[PDB]
């Protein structure tokens, strides 16, 4: 740690130097390792950041922050407005938009460089609301490629989101699950303020700068020390862009603490917010004028991106656990816009998580939070598979805070809430030679950007949570060619092979060709793991029956706009019929359900939607049967009897694909038969942790679902298979007052269902695979 070395000719060097030698890079301040003369040499401030008429053609002075001398361009250190003030040029923002059909790079450049310009707490609505005070940002947005909004990851905090942007991973996977964290294995705490965050043990996955370097692409610095002014960060980027071909980095990142810092104090739309926005825009202008005078403004790819949004949150809107709990001083709480509950460590043997959950469950009529055990949280949040995530979680309502007691105004804004909340949405703008011209694209999740950034730099992305090819429609060229995954298990197509007399399933029933075309509209789902399964055809539906799980992996059926809804006849209530195509040994039995005093059963294809009374008997086949708790049957029967027809009538028919999910380890991935921890009493019948449905129809609703030309439209859910309805505070009332609300909370992407089942959907369509990938990543928000 020898500080006696100098920074002379080493200011913001890109080669990192280890001990004893002192550092002259931007992170040297954060690690307290700079050479004695770092601030003096590298952080000059004299005469400001702008050229004036009088300074034009000046004699070079070492003391100045930036220069207005004739040699500054070749030295790559002019003030960004040099050519405008001195050489009579115009500001980039004043020029009309001209399409960049090919990169116009100076000789020597291997590829167009990438500049990631990141802004903290920049909410999606600032683009429209602040447009008049942001002309540079408006030019980038209007003449490049932009999304109306970009969805952040949960929690909608800085560190989990910036690290998701860099890696393409969910927080539960990269390890930065919050701004404040406690790892029980390390017995250490990660905080916004402190030296523990600098330890590399916390940061999982492979960020973009490591992906680049490992593939021989030079990466500039992503993390900047707070003491480095935004003008110096911009000039450092421009100076690095002026380096010789063999030293010049290809990927750069700028970061602005604003508008977040002001947002917390003044709220998202506080009158004080106009100045920070004008400032961010001025910084954009400086970068753009700086690139123009270096002849790079039609060669560099620029990404203007945010990490999260900002909501109106005051301390008057605070919910206290001391109003629900007796032992509030005997618990540790990560408070605010989310809640994570832990017991206090010493002499607290009476701590019961079940008592804390019960006392936080539907207690006040207007309660502004909901408790959950992390494995019961909506699957779309991907917030469970990490030891740094406490078992007790509190999902707090937008505009609300959670605190322990009145003991614990200053703030008018905050963020961290569910990532589907409007105020939490952020921005995406792509501008440059590889992005499209004057193009608007649909909203997407920030997990997807890492693959795009690799593509823009010709890199091979590390394994991540993005779906490579889903964002090809953003690019003019340098597109990745995606290929469908190969089917691992081929299906069996059984015929009639068994006699009714062979079946002693303890089941009783008073029961004395054009299917694939109508009910399987996008081909059969591909099974991407090793297993034994049968395709079963029926008049009203088709299924893929698992011999190992003794139930369908999937059930596919089309419900037209005009379909008639019938009831289950009184004499068929407890009817279960054997399927003469499937062996009694590969079949479920009624005796297991009679002997399970907590478990009942349901059907994947709804008997309520049968085409005829004759066809209705197929719905009662033992092979359409699935285990269901009585409480869950209330949810499932309402969905099947009421909601499927409602959707068919609203969407001009629907195609439904339903089935079970097994995720006992809550990792978001399909369980192997050895991971199943619950079976129907004294049986091989596994209990699903969740039930899914994929509801597809035509984007052009004037076309019926079964005769659709053009893009598709989808909505999906992953319902938790619970023995009670404590999640729904009005569950004592009629299902029409609570079931649909539950389902909206548990909305999912087709891609989320694919990970959990090992299935591959939409294999036989008239659409391009890139378009199908975009469809699979779609989340229906009801927001
Ligand atoms: C989102 O996308 C994710 C990424 O694809 C998915 O997560 C992956 O899930 C799988 C399955 O669960 C898991 O695979 C297992 O890996 C076990 C070994 O794990 C360690 O190594 C990997 C790989 O390390 C490489 O990459 C990193 C950079 O990412 C690099 O730093 C390493 O040096 C190493 O480099 C090599 O590869 C890179 C390219 O990636 C090259 O550039 C390089 O040259 C080298 O070739 C790590 O990623 C793991 O990291 C976890 O653990 C550390 C320490 O705890 C954390 O810091 C980190 O955040 C991460 O934690 C998360 O995952 C673990 C589980 O791994 C959770 O428990 C935790 O809660 C977090 O969520 C490890 O350090 C291996 O043992 C295992 O083997 C099993 O299967 C084989 C069959 O193949 C059997 O034979 C065995 O018996 C085992 O049963 C299996 O292969 C991945 O590790 C995991 N990756 C990550 C990043 O989490 C995720 O599922 C997906 N989400 C959804 C919902 O789809
Ligand atoms: O801790 C802080 C402020 C300190 N920041 C943290 C993030 C950071 N990122 C970068 N580089 C980016 C560029 C980039 C681009 C792509 C991918 C990764 C990255 C990394 N450089 C410096 C800093 C310093 C904080 C801020 C807001 C808060 N809001 C709140 O509620 O708490 C808050 C705490
Ligand atoms: C839960 O509520 C009951 C009744 O108000 C109370 O007796 C009990 O102490 C509470 N438990 C906790 C842990 O807050
Ligand atoms: Cl946090
Ligand atoms: Zn932030
Ligand atoms: Zn913040
Ligand atoms: Zn699993």
Image (cartoon, rainbow, N blue to C red):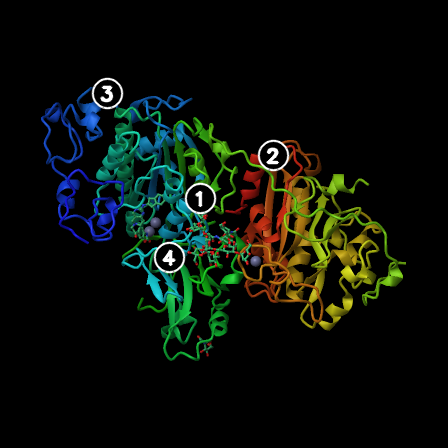
Give the residue number, with chain letter if any, for mark 1: 446
Residue 366 visible, this orientation: no
Q: Is residue 335 left or right of residue 265?
A: right
Q: Is residue 745 left or right of residue 332?
A: right
Give the residue number, with chain letter if any, for mark 4: 202
Nearer to me, 112 or 770? 112
Nearer to me, 234 or 85? 234
Residue 354 in the image: x percent, y percent? 50, 73
- Going from the N terminus, do you reach mark 4 or mark 3 first? 3
- Say few, some or many: other residues with alpha carbon within 10 Å of mark 2 (under 14 / 14 to 19 / 20 or more): some
Give the residue number, with chain letter if any, for mark 3: 89
Inter-mark Cα distance, 2 to 3: 47 Å
Inter-mark Cα distance, 4 to 3: 48 Å
Residue 469 visible, this orientation: yes
Residue 620 in the image: x percent, y percent? 79, 57
- Say few, some or many: other residues with alpha carbon within 10 Å of mark 3 (under 14 / 14 to 19 / 20 or more): some
Quadrant position of residue 87:
top left
Which residue in the rendered view is the most extreme toward the top? Answer: 88
Quadrant of the image for the N terminus?
bottom left
Q: Secondary structure at mark 4?
A: loop
Residue 597 in the image: x percent, y percent? 69, 73
- Going from the N terminus, do you reach mark 1 or mark 3 first? 3
Q: Secondary structure at mark 1?
A: helix
Inter-mark Cα distance, 1 to 2: 23 Å
Q: Residue at x 65, y 51 (%)?
A: 643
**Of the numbered discs in the image, which one, if any, rests on residue 711?**
2
Q: Is mark 1 within 8 Å of ligand 2?
A: no
> Total number of numbered labels?
4
- Going from the N terminus, do you reach mark 1 or mark 2 first? 1
- Going from the N terminus, do you reach mark 4 or mark 2 first? 4
Quadrant position of residue 743:
bottom right
């Amino acid at each position: 740690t020898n500080t006696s070395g100098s920074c002379k000719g080493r200011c913001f060097e890109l080669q990192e130097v280890g001990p004893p030698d002192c550092r002259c890079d931007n992170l040297c301040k954060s690690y307290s390792s700079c050479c004695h003369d770092f601030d003096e040499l590298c952080l000059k401030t004299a005469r400001g950041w702008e050229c004036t008429k009088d300074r034009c053609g000046e004699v070079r002075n070492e003391e100045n922050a930036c220069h207005c001398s004739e040699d500054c361009l070749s030295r790559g250190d002019c003030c960004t407005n040099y050519q405008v003030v001195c050489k009579g040029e115009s500001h980039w923002v004043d020029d009309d938009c001209e399409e960049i059909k090919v990169p116009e790079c100076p000789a020597g450049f291997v590829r167009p460089p990438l500049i990631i310009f990141s802004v903290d707490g920049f909410r999606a609505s600032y683009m429209k609301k602040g447009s008049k005070v942001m002309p540079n940002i408006e030019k980038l947005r209007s003449c490049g490629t932009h999304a109306p909004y970009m969805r952040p990851v949960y929690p909608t905090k800085t560190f989990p989101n910036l690290y998701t942007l860099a890696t393409g991973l969910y927080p539960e996977s990269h390890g930065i699950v919050g701004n404040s964290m406690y790892d029980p294995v390390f017995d250490a705490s990660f905080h916004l303020r402190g030296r523990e965050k600098f330890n590399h043990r916390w940061w999982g996955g492979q960020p973009l700068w490591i992906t680049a370097t490992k593939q021989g692409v030079r990466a500039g610095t992503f993390f900047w020390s707070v003491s480095i002014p935004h003008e110096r960060r911009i000039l450092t980027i421009l100076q690095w862009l002026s380096l010789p071909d063999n030293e010049r980095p290809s990927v750069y990142a700028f970061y602005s603490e604003q508008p977040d810092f002001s947002g917390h104090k003044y709220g998202p739309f506080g009158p004080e917010m106009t100045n920070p926005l004008r400032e961010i825009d001025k910084t954009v202008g400086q970068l753009m004028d700086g690139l123009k005078q270096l002849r790079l403004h039609r060669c560099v790819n620029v990404i203007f991106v945010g990490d999260h949004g900002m909501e109106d949150v005051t301390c008057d809107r605070t919910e206290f656990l001391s109003n629900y709990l007796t032992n509030v001083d005997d618990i540790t709480l990560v408070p605010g816009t989310l809640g994570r509950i832990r017991a206090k460590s010493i002499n607290n043997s009476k701590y019961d998580p079940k008592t804390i959950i019960a006392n936080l469950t539907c207690k006040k009529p207007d309660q502004h939070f909901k408790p959950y055990m992390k494995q019961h949280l909506p699957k779309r949040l991907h917030y469970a598979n990490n030891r740094r995530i406490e078992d007790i979680h509190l999902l707090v309502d937008r505009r609300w805070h959670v605190a322990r007691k009145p003991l614990d105004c200053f703030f008018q804004g905050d963020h961290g809430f569910d990532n589907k909340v409007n105020s939490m949405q952020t921005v995406f703008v792509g501008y440059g030679p590889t992005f499209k011209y004057r193009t608007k694209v649909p909203p997407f999740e920030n997990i997807e950007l890492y693959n795009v950034m690799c593509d823009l730099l010709g890199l091979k992305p590390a394994p991540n949570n993005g779906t490579h090819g889903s964002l090809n429609h953003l690019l003019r060229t340098n597109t990745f060619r995606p290929t469908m995954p190969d089917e691992v298990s081929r299906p069996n197509y059984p015929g009639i092979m068994y006699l009714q007399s062979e079946f002693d399933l303890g089941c009783t029933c008073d029961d004395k060709g054009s299917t694939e075309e109508r009910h399987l509209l996008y081909g059969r789902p591909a099974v991407l793991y090793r297993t034994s399964y049968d395709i079963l055809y029926h008049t009203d539906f088709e299924s893929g029956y698992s011999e190992i799980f003794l139930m369908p992996l999937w059930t596919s059926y089309t419900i037209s706009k005009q379909a008639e809804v019938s009831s289950i006849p009184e004499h068929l209530t407890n009817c279960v019929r054997p399927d003469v195509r499937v062996s009694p040994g590969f079949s479920q039995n009624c005796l297991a359900y009679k002997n399970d005093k907590q478990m009942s059963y349901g059907f994947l294809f709804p008997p309520y939607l049968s085409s005829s009374p004759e066809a209705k008997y197929d719905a009662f086949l033992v092979t359409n049967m699935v285990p269901m708790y009585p409480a869950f049957k209330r949810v499932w029967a309402y969905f099947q009897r009421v909601l499927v027809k409602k959707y068919a009538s609203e969407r001009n028919g629907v195609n439904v694909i339903s089935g079970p999910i097994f995720d006992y380890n809550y990792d978001g991935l399909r369980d192997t038969e050895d991971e199943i921890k619950q079976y129907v009493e004294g049986s091989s019948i596994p209990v699903p942790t969740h039930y899914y449905s994929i509801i597809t129809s035509c984007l052009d609703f004037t076309q019926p679902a079964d005769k659709c030309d053009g893009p598709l439209s989808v909505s999906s859910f992953i319902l938790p298979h619970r023995p009670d309805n404590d999640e729904s505070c009005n569950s004592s009332e009629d299902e029409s007052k609570w079931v649909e609300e539950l389902m909206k909370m548990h909305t999912a992407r087709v891609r989320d269902i694919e990970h959990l089942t090992g299935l591959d959907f939409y294999r036989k369509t008239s659409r391009s695979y890139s378009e199908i990938l975009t469809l699979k990543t779609y989340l229906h928000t009801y927001e």
